Length: 267
Length: 267
Image (cartoon, rainbow over all chains, first blue to last red; front, side, top):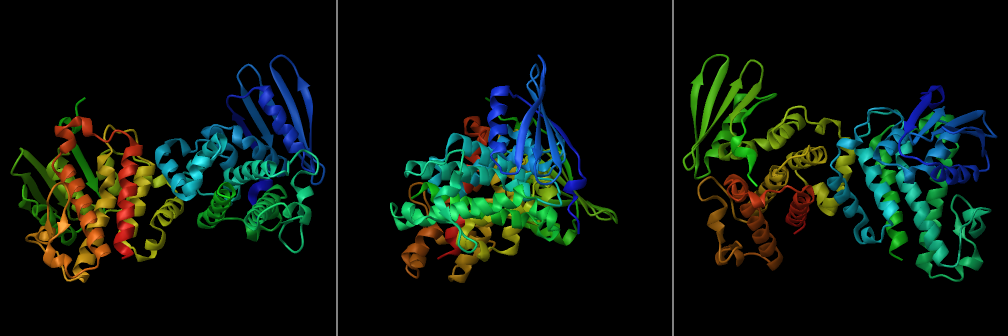
């Protein structure tokens, strides 16, 4: 089989944006070692940026229509798209999140009864649910509505974005509160070694913690890192046999993610 | 406020029926003390039954179009409708179940990703999920899809049907396996007393059981009886302040029901 993402064209418009909101998303995107951005043009009505990959040939055009608040994304749904929409995701309303995650118009996430999707999230998070940050709760509920109404797609891998962005925020605040700030250079990596396939906290940082703190931080970062690396580096384009074509398999990854999120809050 | 159900007309058609399937549903319906049915006409193509209430003036016309398999229901969505569709519910496909529970055409339960609705049910049922009867699992999953895609309704009370029918089946098999068969005359009631607002097993039947068996059977039957009585006797028409206008409140009843179902299986 062949992954269809590299033959696909993206040209979508997202509502309710101002430039102050878009700048940090571009900067976050450019923290990836293969991603950079630049401003291409600016006048009174429109500002256009270009996100490019320094590895594979790829360029994403992002246009803010200032007067209307509309943010347009144009290109292919490859690495620049995956990176930019990941960092954009927590800012989006339900309509916008669905568009970036399923890459179609006329999605149906807006027909899902939100209170029923919330009771789903309440059940899985259990004693973690009241600890959820406002942004996380909204992203996870909106992400559940997107999963619940997803159309038939060849690859569901992008539907894990709400969980992975949520892991990122909780991991960041948890490590920061434990004396391990995560900031722009080095990032998470200054805290972890990687023998075999798993990341474990370096000895000097582990030595300050209890064993359950050590374990949840290491297992959370490993899951976040491996899953996000696979998405950002198009691993399922390079190896189409790894496409998540089964929604039950996607949910298997989502339930694992929910368990990590839960543990990150109750420790 | 006023409940709109008594001003509403129902005329819907359900797919894939044969007469052998419909007869027991009519007979079950006529086990209610205020409900009776009769066959009105029969030829080679169509058989028509009439369900009537002996209390309030109400008549439901049920027509089986034999050649096409279509089962038509015509009347008002009052007591005969509530009783007949309750006993019909476990027989219906997703489209049919949605029609009887929301009373509209063009529902959207068919766009819900079933595997995501299943993982919802798997999470709430926990160690009970592998114990679920085939019919119960299908009804609960289909019922979840109906809740998830329900349109804006003034009264969501009917959306508890999948849970209440499921409680009924598990309660029946559990009591039967414990020496307490539930059959057509007397029914459940020959096993229970009712002091105050709660049903408790009669002493001679309690004396054979362990305390947790006694408690779950009594709390399950109380919930089933009170909730179903309120639906069958139009309590939210008589007292419109009790309409379940909030989907969060409906889900509160559904989660309680799920907990009873769970306990009924793990005892």
